[PDB]
């Protein structure tokens, strides 16, 4: 029931997760606008085999990363 | 994957080198027997 804005709460929680090392799984339910149903939906579909989740999980500011960015590198090396 | 590719290209390189060396040895043996059989 806090009266904190979304941006402030999100940035503070992210700083806490990155520095104090709090478990990010619990922190998902603390941002306003997200309920327990949303957390359960995130947990159920977080490592799906579809291309969407794989692309959005290994995402970098300069394009998709992970195995998708490793395939082009290994092709170039080969 | 990179190490496997390097190993494969190497392996064919030394396979060709060994085949060439065997052919050279066979040619040298043939030349030696040809020059020795003459008398």
Image (cartoon, coloured by chain):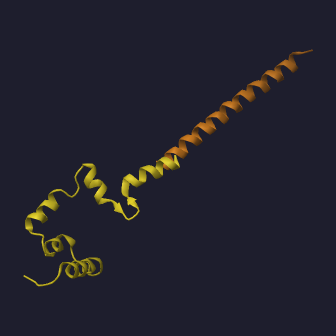
Q: Is residue A22 above or below residue A51?
A: below
Relative horizontal placement of residue A11, taking residue A74 as reference (left or right): left
Q: Position of residue A68 (x, y in %)?
A: 38, 52
Residue at the limit of the structure toward the right, as seen here:
B39
Q: Is residue B14 left or right of residue A20?
A: right
Residue nearer the viewer, A49 or B3: A49
Where residue B29 sits, quadrant-wise, is top right
Q: Residue at x 41, y 62 (%)?
A: A62
**Is the residue A19 above or below the residue B24 in the image?**
below
Residue A29, above or below A41: below
Q: State the image coordinates of residue A60 (x, y, percent, origin top left).
A: 37, 63
B38 relative to A30 in the view: left or right: right
Name the side, left or right, on which A4 lies relative to B23. left
Viewport quadrant of the C terminus of chain B: top right
In percent of the image, x 22 and y 82: which residue is there? A8
Which residue occupies 21% across, 58% down? A46
Tell how many labels: 0
- Pinpoint residue B12: horizontal percent, then vertical percent: 59, 37
Q: Quadrant of residue A57?
A: bottom left
Q: Nearer the viewer, residue B1 or A76?
A: A76
Q: Percent from the top left, x then y, of residue A73?
A: 47, 52
Which residue in the rendered view is the most extreme toward the bottom? Answer: A3
The colour one sees for chain A in the rendered image is: yellow
Chain in orange in the render? B
């Amino acid at each position: 029931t806090s009266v904190r804005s979304l941006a402030q709460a999100v940035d503070a929680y992210g700083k806490a997760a990155t520095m104090l090392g709090m478990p990010k799984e619990f922190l998902w339910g603390l941002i306003p606008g997200i309920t327990k149903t949303d957390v359960e939906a995130m947990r159920q579909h977080f490592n799906d085999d579809d291309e969407m989740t794989q692309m959005l999980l290994w995402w970098t500011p300069n394009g998709p990363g992970g195995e998708f960015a490793a395939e082009i590198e290994v092709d170039s090396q080969t | 994957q990179i190490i496997e590719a390097q190993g494969d290209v190497q392996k064919d390189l030394q396979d060709a080198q060994a085949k060439a060396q065997a052919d050279l040895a066979k040619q040298n043996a043939a030349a030696q027997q040809r020059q020795a059989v003459a008398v």
